[PDB]
Image (cartoon, rainbow over all chains, first blue to last red; front, side, top):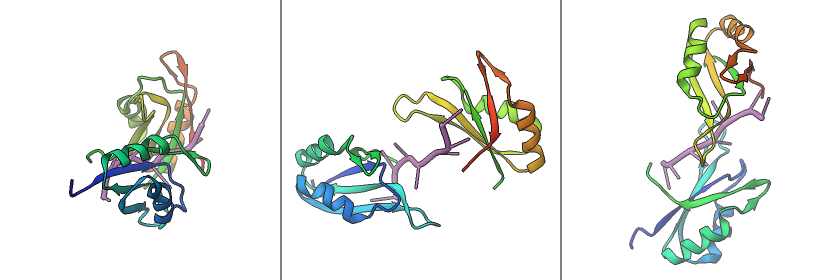
Length: 84
Length: 81
RNA sequence: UUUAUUU
């Protein structure tokens, strides 16, 4: 719908930035927003972020390819965002 | 803040209650956490306690290291970087 | 075997 679908990415590095998210997700389809969550005191990435994709089937393709992807030396976890 | 204490060789079913019961008697404790596998939610075998007072943390460590928890011998120490 | 897990 209008909100799109929100994807949660875990196991980003301390120097990860929005550019790394756009680059990873952009290829699978329309991406409308990205955000890296950063540590209040250090300004480093706390290790996770969010990407909003418009179309469910493109979001599902992204998650299938990127969940388990090795970025630097860490195995990413990616899935649709849950509440909290 | 306080002094962070590392506890290794916790079993799968270990929880915060067991850590509170062990370390509580030695002095002020402000946090306990058991580390769990994100998927299975089973304790991965270690946890942490934060105690406020350096000398009380020392006493807990010297007293509890080698403590037998179920079938397992615990390793307790000041947390390393 | 030394805690970033959902803005």
